Image (cartoon, rainbow, N blue to C red; front, side):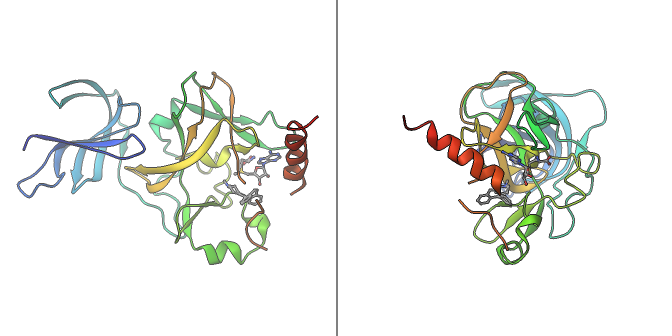
Length: 244
Ligand SMILES: C[S@@+](CC[C@H](N)C(=O)[O-])C[C@H]1O[C@@H](n2cnc3c(N)ncnc32)[C@H](O)[C@@H]1O
Ligand SMILES: CN1CCC(=C2c3ccccc3C=Cc3ccccc32)CC1
């Protein structure tokens, strides 16, 4: 009857008063990120973000949230990608992600850029979002493997991709999950995420506590889709660690 909270398994949530029809519709609805603190507050229709302004969940009293707007004019809307359009605002960063990760040269030799944590956080922490264009498994599997570096399977029907030129931060920085390099001793995994802006995508989630400026890596693996040695090299070394 009063305030409804809808939690997703990823730890994010929708919160506000429902309308006469029991829908999350109004001007005082919020999406709350998995930190249970960073929030997008404002106009939602049936749970879908029309105009969310950056906010902080300051306190909750008997399930009733108290939000304060952040300074400035950061505004967001449900903006699900398509087969060809990655975003209506490719250069508008995600504010939760901006506080937790950054891109820099990978510490892995000859591995291009990598993703690094800004913060010390514990296990199972959502750090970053893997948004991209949505394409079929047929398109990915039927093309040259060298076009599939940024592909990540979403579900039975869809593969997410971050194709050129969006693989460059100067062209696309709305999410950064695609900047995480591979490792066989990763500190992170890809995981399902339901994002108020990007819709259903995947996220990067730590497997264990990480330190500030630690590089974030994920096991990509185990044969690449479509149609490398750096994989083969580390695979062997990883194997050796298991025996005399
Ligand atoms: C999903 S992107 C990761 C970000 C990428 N390094 C960049 O600069 O945009 C995957 C690509 O990064 C490189 N890469 C990822 N892991 C690597 C590794 N362990 N060693 C060498 N290169 C790696 C490969 O070129 C791969 O195609
Ligand atoms: C985030 N995504 C990156 C690409 C990826 C690959 C891949 C694609 C092209 C070239 C190399 C790789 C490396 C490992 C891999 C292994 C198994 C399935 C997919 C992948 C899966 C994870």
